Amino acid sequence: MQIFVKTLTGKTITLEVEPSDTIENVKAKIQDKEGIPPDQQRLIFAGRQLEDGRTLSDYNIQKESTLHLVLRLRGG
Amino acid sequence: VKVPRNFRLLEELEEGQKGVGDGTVSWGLEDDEDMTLTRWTGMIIGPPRTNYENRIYSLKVECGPKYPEAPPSVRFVTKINMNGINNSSGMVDARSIPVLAKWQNSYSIKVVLQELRRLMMSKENMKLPQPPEGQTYNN
Image 1: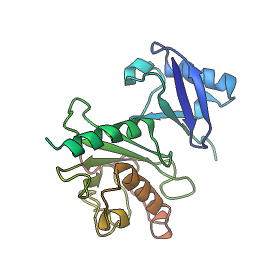
Image 2: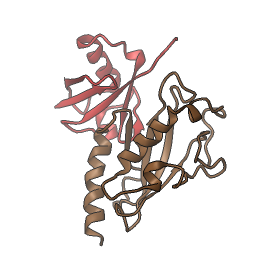
Image 3: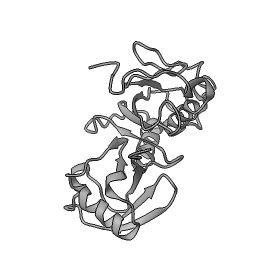
């Protein structure tokens, strides 16, 4: 399914993943195409924070969903 | 059943899930199972370079039967030192917040959260000493 990963910067990227995929893997895919380190990746959905070792189905994330990528500033 | 209230809340649910608007705000059904849409949860991502930097604040919103004609009930769950916010209950004051004092039926929960975050960037709040991160007004 195609999901919309929108960062606080404004840019919205399209990610082709399946519900059975883990956020930890999702981050890696974003790191591959965008180059954003998973360590500083924090996804926000439904007004709550998402985890890493969980699947998209864990938060009931469907297709065409605009996820929010909040940069987790580490060291500054 | 309030047709406009239910219809409006169902629409705002989408905007909350997708986090449409400013971008640094999100909300949605807290219980989720409760389809009465009277128990909403709000999340405000604290703006960097302020006293709310990297602080994920959680709020509780209750839209009454008069919604959206009348202002809903908004209160903070996480301890926050901001003008208009009670230090014991975390309840937000209406006459303190512009959008709550001068509420309009054209407003939404989205605008409320955005306004609150906007006021957090204000000089009168950005330099307010915040208590230990993690403390909640309940539990």
